[PDB]
Image (cartoon, rainbow, N blue to C red; front, side, top):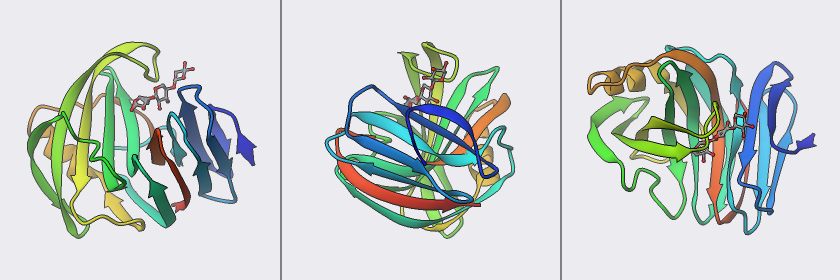
Length: 190
Ligand SMILES: O[C@@H]1[C@@H](O)[C@H](O[C@@H]2CO[C@@H](O[C@@H]3CO[C@@H](O)[C@H](O)[C@H]3O)[C@H](O)[C@H]2O)OC[C@H]1O
């Protein structure tokens, strides 16, 4: 069903839904690995379904519809702890490339596309441990898609070759993000 921001497990899938307190977003958990997001003149939000804890070698499958009108992205999204790391494997995005401002670290080929990899430091920003400072890693698919399989190990290994030390895995989801935009998405994870 439709829920306010929070975390939990639904039909065997972890979910996380976060927003900045601005209105305009409706997040709904559905059967199995399915979730939907519908948004209209939102603020900043990110939510979806997957695993808690994730793993460093998961092959993540997703399918469904992704129709943003503005700034948004569809990604494999997760965290590690000790050290604290936020990471995104971006499969599709809307009007803004979310790696803008991050430092390019190279390229990796995975699951049918080249990806550009990046990192940036986030300073005194929201996180799974509260306000914190942490590196944020990106891997941005060149050939955008809304269904596919992601071999996370290829991305983790590419980042590691440029200095990522992944700590203890925390959640790991397929997420829809929006940033002052509108859209809809209906995604099934497995
Ligand atoms: O109540 C606390 C939650 O609000 C907190 O949630 C996390 C806060 O950070 C969220 O981060 C996304 C960090 O980066 C941008 O990439 C996202 O836009 C931030 O908002 C994250 O998605 C939430 O899980 O967890 C700790 C709780 O105590």
